[PDB]
Amino acid sequence: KLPPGWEKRMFANGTVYYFNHITNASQFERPSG
Image (cartoon, rainbow, N blue to C red; front, side):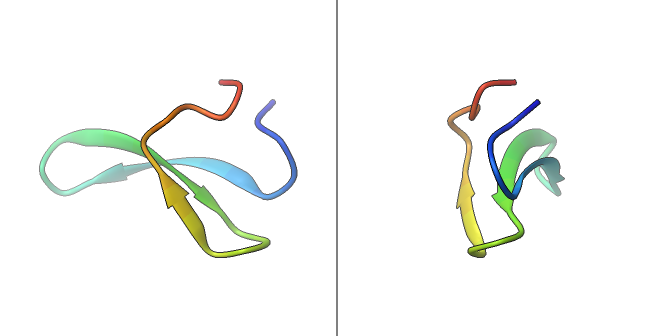
């Protein structure tokens, strides 16, 4: 799946994003998934 800490999530405007739960980083750019 996604690299260390990265987890697929979703935003109130109706879109998917990615959150890194080990660093608190957040991106739309899909980290290998």
